[PDB]
Amino acid sequence: DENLYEGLNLDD
Image (cartoon, rainbow, N blue to C red; front, side):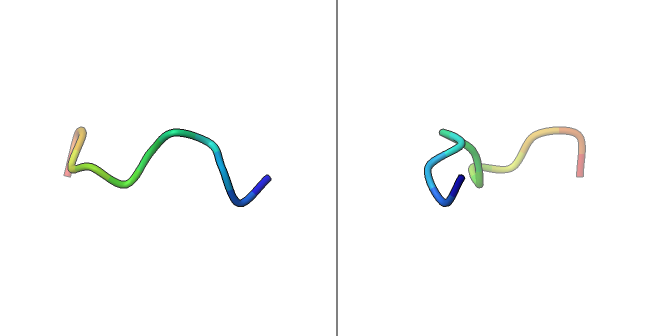
């Protein structure tokens, strides 16, 4: 959901 434990600048 709105959790996903992401954001935090991966392959971008």
